[PDB]
Length: 313
Image 1 (cartoon, rainbow, N blue to C red):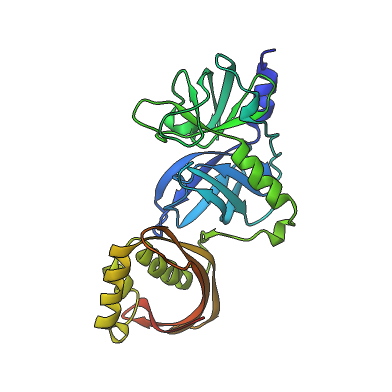
Image 2 (image 1 turned 180 degrees about the vertical axis):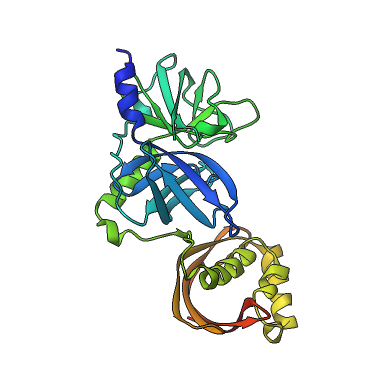
């Protein structure tokens, strides 16, 4: 009852390279992921959280654009990505942590920069002190394989590698049950109907405009008023806004989940961009989580695009 090389090679064809880029096309993070649907890939949240643009590379070299993050869990360092198109990458069958015993053998597969690394090991413990639900392994899985699948001797995905998720030198993996729950919920929706929770951009002809809106929302999320006011014309700055931001940044920890950013209209010195995002409270006193559906006007000032008006509901 041991997973053979032939099976490992076949399962490895579902493992992909996940690369996140900043607005200047620089690589900010890179790791592994795996297909769990035709256009759905599981990975770590840390590999994509700072990616303005995210790309997936399959074992055959094919590169796919990421449309956005459809599910995520910060405490479990978990993310589910949706590609802009359905890919030819075969989804992997997911198992459960309920079948695991301590001492049982596992195989982790990761994609280096798009060739595979196979790491062998065993289950040390069915819990990890400090984590709500994690599995401890007897030895380490390399940083480059993070976000990749962990298989049992039957070939089912029982975990997801998560480099640095616990205390230093603790080797912990997240149970596949969490990804299976997301896949089951999303299974009831067609591909085109799956909704984005945290939007990632593509380097297309609309990038210059969509990025202003992406940057200004990201600045509110990072508690960065200097970047927030830098995204708008000098005219839009108000002392009252600056004061309101100080209270918001010190009172709460907030997540700004972007659903969509789209150019409505554009020209050489003027543009309109629509956007949808939610504000979710992670910590602090009472806060009513809410959705913002807006549209803003942009103008080119000394070459740099800036927001000169907005309307939100």
